[PDB]
Image (cartoon, rainbow, N blue to C red; front, side, top):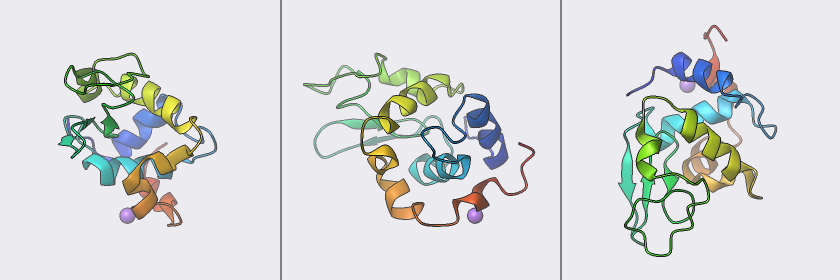
Length: 129
Ligand code: NA
């Protein structure tokens, strides 16, 4: 499913992402925008053989099992395909684990390169939150 901006903002807020680990909602929406263009079905393969999945482009090397990443850790205890659902619940539960890992949102290269230090608040402007 491709989410609308405000629709995603509302869903993430509902799933407890607003200010989670002190990252405001604007951050999560910005990240999702640039990682997957708000599409829960986005997949991208990496040169190391791992693949990123879903709206937050979660990587198969550490967080999910896709059966084809040798030496995967599967730290969110899920198949990667679960990350492609129209329901963002598992994506969200796993993102919380990631962002708590030590590097916070720097784990998401597009957040770091495109959202960090910007007025991320603009991503939720106009929504009924
Ligand atoms: Na904008």
